[PDB]
Image (cartoon, grey):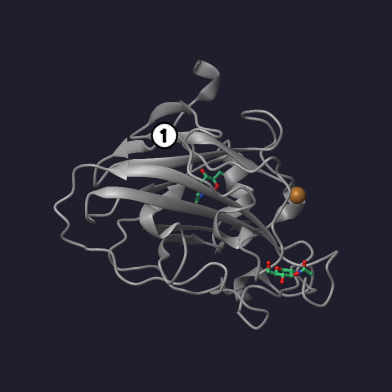
Amino acid sequence: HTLVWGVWVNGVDQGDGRNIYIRSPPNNNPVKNLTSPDMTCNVDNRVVPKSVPVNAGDTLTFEWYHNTRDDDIIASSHHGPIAVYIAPAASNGQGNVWVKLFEDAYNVTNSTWAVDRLITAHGQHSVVVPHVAPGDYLFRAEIIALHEADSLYSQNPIRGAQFYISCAQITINSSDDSTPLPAGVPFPGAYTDSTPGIQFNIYTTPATSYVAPPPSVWSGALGGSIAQVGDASLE
Ligand SMILES: *[C@@H]1O[C@H](CO)[C@@H](O)[C@H](O)[C@H]1NC(C)=O
Ligand SMILES: *[C@@H]1O[C@H](CO)[C@@H](O)[C@H](O)[C@H]1NC(C)=O
Ligand SMILES: [Cu+2]
């Protein structure tokens, strides 16, 4: 159970975004139903009053929390991958609109899941704003927690993969549009029971064999990381 507090831009906190620039749900409960419209932007998908201004090449950082800011972030049991998608705001996340800008599952070297390191980074992970057409966008951050993913929610509704999904309203102002945004996948839609990554046993199978759900990351992506870029105690 985890939620988004806000975002930083080039290492500068934009302040609390909850129900302001984030289309926040009422609580930190996971989405589990792969055919639910909750898969798009979670349970309360509506326009919020603000959109964060960025320019192509900026670092956009998501800051997650559990109950209060800079807490335990998310339970350690929730080992799993982390991804970020983008889509034009006008779609409302409907249709084949979601392009992937980031994927992190398991780092072989450190023997750490993305989630594990998100805790160490005080809830912070980032992406670099790609050179797309100026305008309004939704950035969809998605954490998959695999601790009950040896079962499927369709077969057993009290188990299965857990999605923590947060959509942020972002206005790209300055971009040459040299990497115009391609076609994407649908949410709900891109993940099914058969999709690699959805069903997995993290207690028996080695993490080095885990394959995260497609699609793959777009060439137009300029990269990102899981790592603290800002100190919230300084505020
Ligand atoms: C999952 O969501 C779909 C679409 O909203 C709905 O038909 C179905 O009732 C849901 N399944 C469960 C078990 O809640
Ligand atoms: C691995 O762990 C060390 C600390 O134990 C950290 O300094 C290093 O950045 C980690 N490597 C990554 C994030 O790939
Ligand atoms: Cu949880």
Q: Which residue is mark 1?
A: 50
The quadrant holding residue 130 is bottom left
Side of 46 relative to 35 (left or right): left
Q: Residue at x 22, y 49 (%)?
A: 134
The spot of residue 67 in percent (x, y) is 71, 33
The spot of residue 220 in percent (x, y) is 27, 64
- Kindly identify the amino acid type of the residue bearing the numbered disc 1: Lys
The quadrant holding residue 121 is top right
Side of 66 relative to 226 (left or right): right
Q: Is mark 1 within 8 Å of ligand 3?
A: no
Q: Residue at x 71, y 74 (%)?
A: 200
Query: Looking at the image, is 222 positioned above or below residue 208?
Result: above
Q: Residue at x 13, y 52 (%)?
A: 176
The quadrant holding residue 19 is top right
Query: Looking at the image, is 104 positioned above or below residue 11?
Result: below
Q: Residue furthest toward the bottom?
A: 194
Nearer to us in this view, 28 or 95: 95
Q: Residue furthest toward the top?
A: 235
Q: How many marks?
A: 1
Indicate the secondary structure of the residue bearing disc 1: loop
Side of 214 relative to 71 (left or right): left
Query: Looking at the image, is 192 positioned above or below residue 72?
Result: below
The spot of residue 60 in percent (x, y) is 38, 42
Nearer to us in this view, 214 or 233: 214
Q: Pointer 1: residues within 10 angstroms few (<14), some, or many (20+)?
A: some
The spot of residue 36 in percent (x, y) is 65, 65
Residue 111 in view (yes/no): no
